[PDB]
Amino acid sequence: KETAAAKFERQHMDSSTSAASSSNYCNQMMKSRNLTKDRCKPVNTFVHESLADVQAVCSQKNVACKNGQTNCYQSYSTMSITDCRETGSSKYPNCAYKTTQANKHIIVACEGNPYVPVHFDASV
């Protein structure tokens, strides 16, 4: 049973890549990190940083999470991300995603001792 902290890592964390590798990168990852399982996930962004530099966002500028809450942090720093937005042509079983690559600020929600990222909230 995945602890949230690792679930986050499975849906959000690809450190082994500098950035998107192609464009069916999205399709490879969605699939490969089980997001396309019980349905196709609407959208999912992936961070291309070390877990260590990401977990340390929990000590960076504290912001309100989109949903109204208060355990969210935004990186002081810019970080490379790939947004997997799903498309029109996407019919789970076959979820089709569009690789949109960027190098921007992540805002995540932190929880637990150790206080790690748990939810990816947004990116600006």
Image: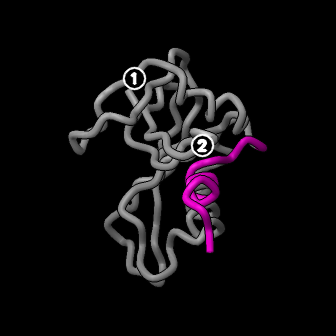
- The amino acid type of the residue labelled 1 equals Asn
Check disc 2 and report its element: helix, strand or loop: loop
Q: Which comes before the other along the chain, label 2 or label 1?
A: 1
32 over 69 or under it: above or below: below
Left or right side of 35 for 6? right
Residues at circles 2 and 1 in contact by the CB criterion of under 8 Å = no
Callout 2: few (<14), some (14-19), or many (20+) C-alpha neighbours within 10 Å? few
Q: Can you identify the residue that label 2 sits on?
A: 113
**Start-end of magenta stretch:** 1-16
At a point 47% along the width and 31% down the height, the residue shown is 106
Q: What number is the disc on residue 50?
A: none
| Pair 2/1: label in front | 2
Q: Can you identify the residue that label 1 sits on?
A: 62
At a point 47% along the width and 60% down the height, the residue shown is 97
- The amino acid type of the residue labelled 2 equals Asn
Q: How many numbered callouts?
A: 2
Image quadrant of residue 25? bottom right
**Where's residue 20, x and y in %?**
64, 43
Image quadrant of residue 62? top left
At a point 52% along the width and 68% down the height, the residue shown is 35
